[PDB]
Image (tube, rainbow over all chains, first blue to last red; front, top):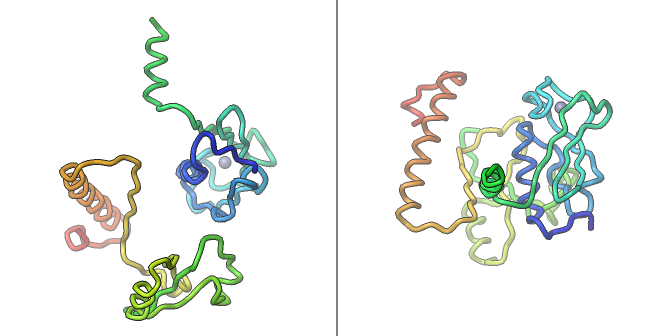
Length: 104
Length: 109
Ligand SMILES: [Zn+2]
């Protein structure tokens, strides 16, 4: 089990990460709780990449789990793409409210 | 392509393609409309996933929207939201068809 289902249903997290990727995901079906940190995410770059804004990517992206979040990073040349983060805990409005109180 | 009375279906999630084009009865099936209905009534526990045979020749399908929101709302909000949503989806599809597809916005709307 590479996924800890203590944050969000794995299907919902995959739905979020797919929504981030405007381009169609090729192997969306095989992402499960025991492979999502291993298999590269091959993407059909019909549209420009949603992260690097280029025409396409030479190498597929990859997912990592860290600090209760998903880190999306490109293989091969790291600086050629932007690192992306998907959170899993907290209503975003609650984070905003915490920041606003935080200012005093 | 003008009409197709038979529907391609999957039996479960995770079907490999090599079974999909080979038409493996253990994963995929073809159902005639009346026979599809008969199978559905006769199998209340059936797991069926509608799909297509070949996108190269039969990419034309009806327009369908899916909305799955984890929030239970009353009937009034339900109806006002569904009418509004169909309004904006009609506006968007008409705008795109007029921009690129060259279709008449009123016709599609
Ligand atoms: Zn990129």
